[PDB]
Image (spheres, coloured by chain):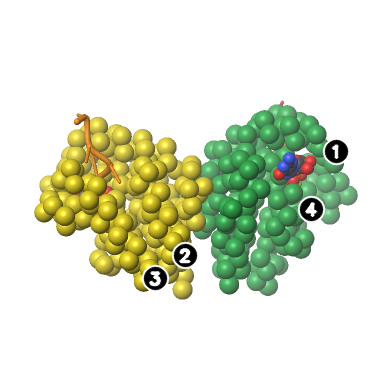
Chain colours: A green, B yellow, C orange, D red
Amino acid sequence: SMKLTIPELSLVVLIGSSGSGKSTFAKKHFKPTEVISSNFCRGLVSDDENDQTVTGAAFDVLHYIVSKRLQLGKLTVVDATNVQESARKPLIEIAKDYHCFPVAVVFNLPEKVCQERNKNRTDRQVEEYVIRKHTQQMKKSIKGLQREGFRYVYILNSPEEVEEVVFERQP
Amino acid sequence: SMKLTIPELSLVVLIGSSGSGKSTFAKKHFKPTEVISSNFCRGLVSDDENDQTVTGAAFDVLHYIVSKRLQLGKLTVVDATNVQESARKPLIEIAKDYHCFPVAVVFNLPEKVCQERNKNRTDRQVEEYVIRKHTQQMKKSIKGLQREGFRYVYILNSPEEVEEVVFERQP
DNA sequence: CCTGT
DNA sequence: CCTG
Ligand SMILES: Nc1nc2c(ncn2[C@@H]2O[C@H](COP(=O)(O)OP(=O)(O)OP(=O)(O)O)[C@@H](O)[C@H]2O)c(=O)[nH]1
Ligand SMILES: Nc1nc2c(ncn2[C@@H]2O[C@H](COP(=O)(O)OP(=O)(O)OP(=O)(O)O)[C@@H](O)[C@H]2O)c(=O)[nH]1
Ligand SMILES: [Mg+2]
Ligand SMILES: [Mg+2]
């Protein structure tokens, strides 16, 4: 298996293009309340998880919930693309404020896999150019993650590696 | 600082070209008996740390010492280039034999930096082609380290990052 | 340096 | 999708 060690008090930041399987992954490995999703927050503020015009409010809400959880010492997983440094920056800062270990889990999957999954989705889709861009941003992000403040950086390089992941939570 | 978390029982594998500063780094961060060096082993078997013809015997000795230490539950740092997969393979296997966690620390420095340092050494030098080769092998190695069995993979991307390292030995 | 042979 |  692919064992990923994380401390009991972690902020797990999922990094991946739309279609890379972040939400599917989060549901398999974590409790529902441990996972806070940017799309869910778009729904919380606007009724519409697909409404990009409420992104600002959605991430304000996400960051707020993350802060409340870390204040209470609860492990939290951020289910958003997190492919822009500007998106990861405030998450690292919140983790620092509450002495929480930031962990990066990167879905380094081929653009074509994400595009294929997106084409076959029935829940929500994005345009092809979005996935092309997210994949490029994800790839450019990998080198600098440790320096950004991620204490553990785990890169998953194929669907096979994603499937094999087992988290080892250390108390 | 660049905080690198490692378990009390770790096999820390330094990965870097000649001239990348492995031995300097090892002395700064670890007690002498925690560090086992391939060049020191060349000296043990032949009187000459620079004798490349005794490489087989030197690594036999290094592996034997690593095995004894991990068996005794002692943190161990391997100071060798470790830029070939075939070199890392037995280290991972010995770690697994004794339920020890392998940690990779990669000196991902520009070839030019290593060459300049090499040029100014008075203790021992290698030819430029050696460093060019080591650097290429190091860079080609990075992606696959987690899959090889390294439970923690830390990549240092500049002399500034190397200098900033602080190990956090979790009990 | 896990060896330009 | 932190909005080409
Ligand atoms: N075959 C296969 N399909 C998967 C896997 N993971 C996710 N999928 C499918 O890919 C599609 C996208 O998966 P999601 O988990 O929603 O992807 P996401 O990264 O959360 O995408 P966004 O929310 O748009 O950012 C879904 O229809 C899944 O059923 C996988 O591991 N294997
Ligand atoms: N400026 C600077 N010089 C360094 C640093 N680390 C090592 N050096 C110099 O670079 C040269 C090589 O350093 P070593 O620690 O011996 O490098 P190594 O990786 O062990 O090299 P090999 O034993 O040949 O594989 C030495 O002369 C060091 O003094 C550093 O962090 N900063
Ligand atoms: Mg999702
Ligand atoms: Mg050395």
Q: Which residue is mark 1?
A: A122
Chain for disc number 1: A
Which of pointers 4 and 1 indicates the residue nearer the eye?
1
Left or right, B155 with reference to A44: left
Beta carbon of the mark 1 residue lies under 8 A of ligand 1: yes
Whole-percent x, y for residue A121 in the image: 81, 37
Circles 3 and 2: CB distance less than 8 Å? no
Q: Which residue is mark 3?
A: B73
Query: Mark 2 to mark 1: distance in Å?
Result: 45 Å
**Which quadrant of the structure image shows residue A12?**
bottom right
Query: Mark 4 to mark 3: distance in Å?
Result: 47 Å
Which of pointers 3 and 1 indicates the residue nearer the eye?
3
Q: Which residue is mark 2?
A: B99
Looking at the rendered structure, which numbered label has been put on residue A41? 4
Q: Can you see residue B60?
A: yes
Q: Do the dots labelled 2 and 4 sit on one chain?
A: no
Query: Mark 2 to mark 4: distance in Å?
Result: 42 Å
Query: Mark 3 to mark 1: distance in Å?
Result: 53 Å
Residue type pointed to by label 2:
His
